[PDB]
Length: 120
Length: 121
Ligand SMILES: CN(C)C(=O)[C@@H](NC(=O)c1cnccc1-c1ccc(C(F)(F)F)cc1)c1cc(C(F)(F)F)cc(C(F)(F)F)c1
Image 1: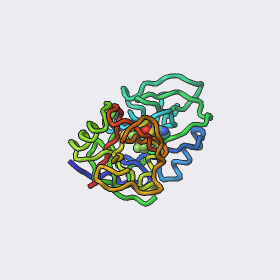
Image 2 (image 1 turned 90 degrees about the horizontal axis):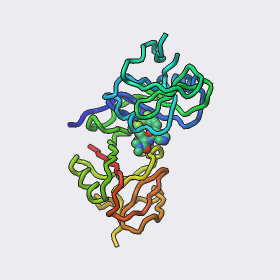
Image 3 (image 1 turned 90 degrees about the vertical axis):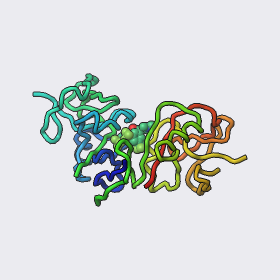
């Protein structure tokens, strides 16, 4: 059964109506967030293991929009339970995504590659 | 930054510039990989444009694509376009594995490997 996906800009991957773009130039969390904002987007937000099962295929670790009450996303929403295994890697208030559905606590100032996400 | 729809594609496939891609991690020889994609109304990965398929720069590891040597051409019988892939020998054979960036590694067609299927409506 075929269906259309998006909408998304042309250079973004579309999957279950979310749009993803990988950035390989390393930036700290704040610079990564600013980069995504300049593309009318945000850093990766993880909300569903089903809608976002493609994240099982992501290799290496990349900034997502999770920051430190509890951890929260850029949009102010809380991290849903039973989505990510949080592991402590560095003293930090930001998190990297790693497969499969892990979040590494990371110094916000450390340069990393990053994933932007859009949903119209 | 202009928005457009991508596809159509089945829901469990990645869509990029209106092509649909699916990665398969259960390793199969080239022929069984071809048959698996066919059972999904698809073919093994065909590389026809660096610009429309620039996401392939981000593909890690090595995966069957639909490129074969008649003792190079694609499953559909079309010939490999120039200026697309750098073909490197690895294991004696008549089939090729895709690797980043826009490389093809020659591989025995009977060797089990992961594979990428591609659909286009
Ligand atoms: C599945 N295999 C065998 C890989 O090679 C994976 N590579 C990396 O994740 C990968 C490897 N090095 C650098 C960057 C990436 C990467 C990071 C974020 C995204 C995202 F923007 F999507 F979030 C996509 C790729 C892979 C996974 C996926 C996805 F989306 F399913 F996760 C798509 C591809 C693509 F089609 F683009 F090539 C490749």
